[PDB]
Amino acid sequence: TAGTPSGNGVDYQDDELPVYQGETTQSLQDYLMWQVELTPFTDTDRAIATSIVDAVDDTGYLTIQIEDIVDSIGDDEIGLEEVEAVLKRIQRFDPVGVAAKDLRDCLLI
Amino acid sequence: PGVLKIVKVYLAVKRRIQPGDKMAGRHGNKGVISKINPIEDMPYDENGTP
Amino acid sequence: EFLKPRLVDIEQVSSTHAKVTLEPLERGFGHTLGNALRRILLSSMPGCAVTEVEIDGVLHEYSTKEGVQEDILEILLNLKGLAVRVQGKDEVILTLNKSGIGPVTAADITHDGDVEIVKPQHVICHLTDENASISMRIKVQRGRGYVPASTRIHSEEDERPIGRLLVDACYSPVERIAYNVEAARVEQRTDLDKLVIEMETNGTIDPEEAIRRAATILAEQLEAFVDLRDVEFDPILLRPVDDLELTVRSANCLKAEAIHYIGDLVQRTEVELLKTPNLGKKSLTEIKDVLASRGLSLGMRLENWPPA
Image 1 (cartoon, rainbow over the protein chains, first blue to last red):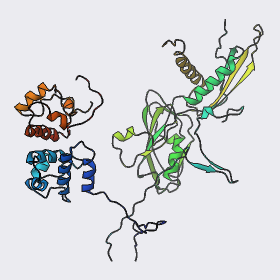
Image 2 (image 1 turned 45 degrees about the vertical axis):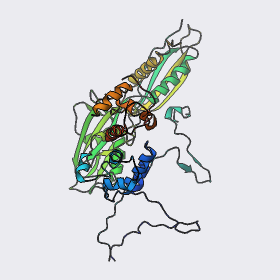
Image 3 (image 1 turned 45 degrees about the horizontal axis):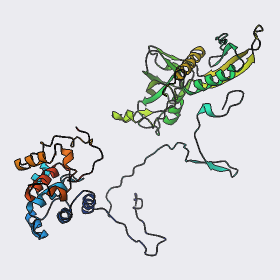
């Protein structure tokens, strides 16, 4: 072996009985929830926000239909007009354009 | 067998003295800097050398 | 009532060493004046010093040049001690170009319009190989005190190319100062003192000029004592409320509810706003829908509110 790499980054939890323990990682959904928790939303608004951010894919686009989201709520007075407003508020988060229904909406936002 | 290319990068920086740094002689006398005084504030002899 | 000192018998031992004398002084004024002048001279005296150097073939301070004995770091350290004088300019550029065998000094620096090298024997490099060439451009700036090369960040406003080497700047020509108080030769007066100030510089500044500058600084500082006396920001907010393109039906309601700006809209909670007359469940959602398009959720809490 003419050229050998230096050791890659690795570690193991020491001085702790449950060895290697763990380490939490921040994903897109976790960051979206963290942002949601720090904006003024009603209880219904919070529920709608959680429901719509649960459906965010890895690429940042919504996989489920808005009408399907309304059906998922399964409660009166939560018609598509309210969920549209909540989703449009959610779209303007740190990854601007996240939770977009299609490419057109993403470019528009 | 797995790797394909390796790149190694070196960075060099200059560390200057500051109040937080530690300084010690070779007689067991150690300590940390408390303040970096200006020249005109330090004591001087009759020749004006601080 | 009080006698006044006059600068008499100014004498120059050497190019750097010098003596300044003030003959008439009162009982206690000698030490006060001496210490004040020493502090002013050692603290704040203007001068010119090397700011950055750009060598031909090098890229960073931690490199080497084929044909020169020293590293670029030692070249910069030697250049840091260069003593120059500039008239009428603060950003002169001193170009240097020399090839051959032997040490290179400040003597071979190209003769600029108004640039004087007080010490022309300052060795800054050593050339060892016959066919070796060196060529740099030295920028000299005028300053007042010690400025490290890391504190200045404003120089990063414009991109600097790879190859410009930043050196520290001292700007202080004065290196050592002492003073003594001796009995004056004036016999008609009861008891007078005399002040002798000895200074060691790098030859950049005149002794008399330094004394005048220190005295002027002291007087300008003392001028203040002679008369004491003395005994909603984000542009998205504060916009007209008729920028959201709301319905006609909500247009009348906002006027009745005394909402005239975008900012005052965002400070209302859902529970109490619904109690307002004839809002409508579906119409209120459109107000939230439009305000969501701007990123301002309903119910924000500000501190102060100007009329505009």
